[PDB]
Image 1 (cartoon, rainbow, N blue to C red):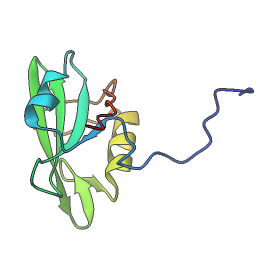
Image 2: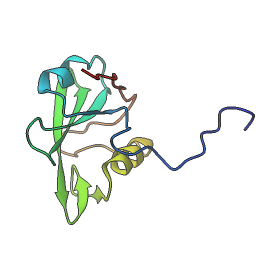
Image 3: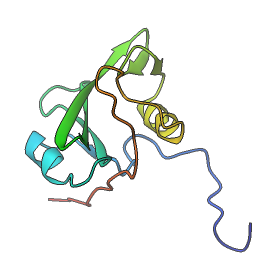
Length: 116
């Protein structure tokens, strides 16, 4: 507590999420990754509604797709009503994306203000 270091709010919406880079191409999603942990969520370029998570793990670019079922966004069965809440809560709980792959969320990669 103090005069600074207190961001009073609930969260930022999916659009304002820095880890959410938008509908950027597959190349741009894989090239910005460097260590095991770097992750970003994009939307499929041309397919509105299909969000692709790109996380670098085990030396590979691990690309997962967010399925919208039962009115919830999910990677491996269990899902949340909102993507920003899905990733945020999944990150803070250190839960694995899919048990098939075994990838965890650490240090999210921010985005640039590409007005072009």
